[PDB]
Length: 520
Image (cartoon, rainbow, N blue to C red; front, side, top):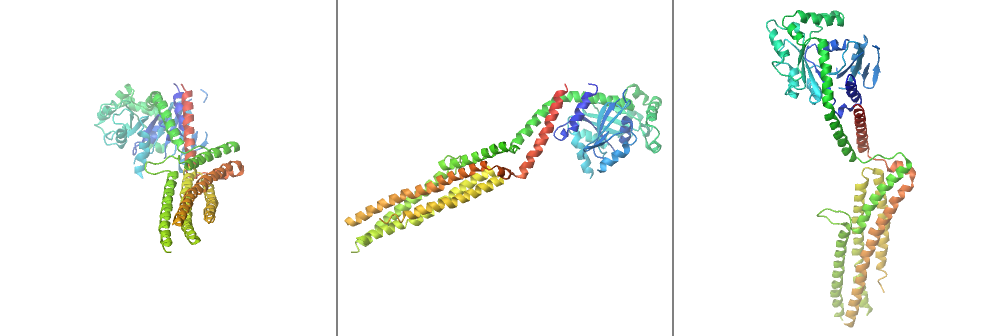
């Protein structure tokens, strides 16, 4: 309760988690000449977002990005150095008088469009308490500070007001200031406080900061309007310090369960989104082999589905096997047309008044040779298209795997298609082997059937079965050649990087859980 509640969040902040996760905080809103700079001086005792981690010392540190310096006089120079070097700068101070309190200071309001958005970036989170610093003589209605605070915190339930430099309050309107601090104008759950600090003329001398601590108490003890606010514990820096730490702790404690609820669901969101980008490539050579082999197996199964007309397809389209059945139907029609036209051609020679007629049927049969070979070509093209479309679906992220697959797909096409043409072509050399009209016409039906049957079977044999077979064999052999694993498993840098960032994000999220679970 004492100090740990604060130690908790700040280390979660040091985790770099704050980008994935909202951490309980007091954000310090600065105005134009609000003198906020001086108020922090009062608490600390000594621009892109500054984190003030304050710890009060018996026994008796600055970090820009990764690096740090150690000592209290030198602090001023280290600050301005780090800046020149929107990223968090943390400052940890420890002395007997400094409060136990962590604040985050933002650039004061005034390329301005950007500062609002930076400020809004912190303020809009219901886990942020907006700590508004405005000079007390100016109307609070006009101040940009409150307006921002109000834009984000409509009900004033996460905002705290600091009125500054109560000297320059126009005489006659002291009671208006008192109504604001007493909460009578714009109502804040967490309230108002008023403080007096280092003005223009003392910052030039820079007389001692602890002497100023005694300069407040006599300003408020003697002031006729504000003496009443001190009796009510709403005036001075030491009072301000106590209230802030009281309020911070109350916030952190209130916030915890809704936060442990928030980390879980974020963890999920990252892990769900992490799924879409595959998995890591194993360091171990053997695990590498199993990884590649599994990838080969799924390619090889998608190829298999094609071979069997089993592959999963769209509602309108049809399976490759079926598309080849339609080619094969077109082919039968070609046989049918060839058969009858040969019938017409033969009657035009027999009643034109033996082996002259044998030759004529033979020529009618040979004419089918090119339809057959075209069909060979037409079908390999379909399968090649199919096989490469599988290689796309499986190996896009692994371009060498895809490159290699394509290469085999092409190499085995050239080989199988050659073999298929050979057998088709040779089939039409093997073929040279009114009672005459019939004998020839019956001979003609036999030959066609032979041809109508074998040609598709050869096409199917070489360009679908043997083709798929060999390719699968070829791919499966990649797993034997270990010194190519490094090349084959090279993957796209785009998704390779996307995964890398998420794993890092998820890592920091996991540490967070760990430290949060440790605390109770």
